[PDB]
Image 1: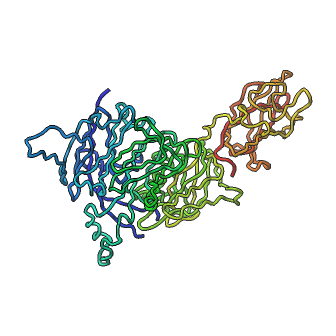
Image 2 (image 1 turned 60 degrees about the vertical axis):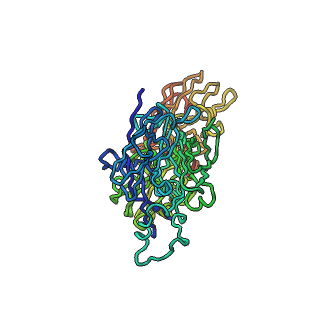
Length: 631
C-alpha cells in the first residue's frame, strides 16, 4: 500500500444567487464563492457533475486518508483579499522574523500555495466512522467572509477507504449540508445596494426595516429558497450526511429528515431523530433510508423553517415505491426521435430538481411527447412532474396524458379509476410544482410516454418516476409456491367422482397425489382454465406441463391464451397476424418455456387448450410479476 500527495487546484470567484423555483422581480446578488479549477493555468472551470451539484453555492470537496499529504495551490480573483484556512493547517519551523508574522493573506492575482502532512490529529478513530468532517474558510475577515460565501468542506478518512475513481464509494454516497443564516451588512454589499435595485427610483429604506438577508437567506448552502438541487441517493446504499453549522451566535440549527432515523458515533454509536447543529460543530452522521419516495430536510426551529428551510430530497431503489432514478440512473438516457427541440434540449437534462439555466425539457410544439426506456420490464407506481423557470417567465405543463409500451411495438393509452375514456393528469401550477401523481394502479412498462394536453409558454417539464422492480421477472408468479390460493383459480369445468377430484386448484407445475392436476369434465377445444390475480400483473409466459395419472399419460399439445382487466369479458392473445398457436407439451412430465412476444398486461389469465393427447390435463405455472395493481 502507498501514501498519496493530493493537490487541489482551487480559486475564489463570484456570480451568485438564483431564486428561480416558482414562488417577475427577483434580485441579483454578487457574493464570493470557492471554485475548483483543473491545473496551475486556472482555465477549465471544472464542471460540477451530477454527483456533487448539491454542493452548488459553497466550495469543492478536499479529501485525504490518514498518513497522507494535502496540497492547495490557491489564486484569489476578487476585490477584498481573501485566504485559505482550516484546523490542521500545519505551518512549520521558525524564521529570522519580528515577533512571528504567521499571517495568511492572499492578494488578488497572487498565488499562495501551501501543503502539509495530515497527521492523525485530524483523523477519525476506531470508535468513530470511515471519515470525519472539517471546515475550511477564509481567515482574513472570519466574521464577514463566512457570510461572504467562503464556506468549504474537508474530509479526513481512514486508510484504504478512497479509490482510483476519486473519493470513496464502498457502500457510501456522501452529502454535505452547510447551515448558516447569511447577512449583507458584511462583504462589499455597497457594490450591490446602489449597483442593482436603485437608479433614479431610489432613496427607499436605509437600514430601517429593509433587512435584506433576514428578508430571505436561511441557508442550507446558498441555493436556499425552500429547495436545493442534487440530493440524490439510493434507499439501501447507506448515506453519510456531513452536517456543518457556521455563522453568528443565534445560528443553532436543529435539523431533521422526516420519516427517517440516523446513527451518530461519539463514544459508541447511538440513535437520533434530529440533531442540534452548533456553529463550529462539524458532524458526520449516517442513515439507511429504507423508506422510499420523496422527503425533505428541515431546520425544525419554527421561524427558521417559515423563511427557507423546507428543502427536498429523493431516495430511489427497491421496497417498493421508490424512484426509478431520474437523478441517479443514467447520464443521458432516452428521449424522443423528433418531438423535442429548443437548443436547451430534450431529456438529456430533463430531470427533477436539476439546477442551472440550461435546465429541463422545452418545446413550443403542440404535438409533443418525451420517452424513457427503463431498459427492463419495470414497476412504475407514479410520476413526479415539475416545471422550469425562464427570463422572468413561469413555464410548465398544466395537463398531460400517459401512454406506455411493454415491447417497443404496440402502445396504448391509459385509464385511471373507472375515469372515463382516457386518464387526464394534472401537472404543475408553476415552475416548481412537485405534483407527485401516483398511478392509482398499474403500468408494467419498459417505455413510458408523457404527452402534454396543455402548457404555459412552452411544453416544459422535468420529472422523476416512482416504482421499483417486479421481480425482474423470468421468475415464477406463485403457482408452485402457492402464493396464488386454491380458491383463486377456477376453470370452465372439473372432473370429479369419488376416487378423484381433478379441480382447477390442482393445476400446479410439480404436484403429486391421486388427483394431481386439473382436468375438465369432458374434452372440448372451447374449454378453459382461469387464474384470477387479486391485483394487476405482467406475464412473461405460461409454463405448461402434463399429468402422470398412473393409468395413462396425459398432457396438452397446443393451446391459446386470453386476457381481461374486468374479469368477465375477454380480449385474446394474437401474433403479428392471427391468434397464437402455442407449442405445448409432449409428455407426463417436462415443463415448457412458453413466452409472449408482447409481454401480457392482465389481471385475469385464461389457458384455452386446442390439441391434446388422450385427455386434456394440465399442471402449470405463470412467469411474472406486478407493476402496479388494477387501472
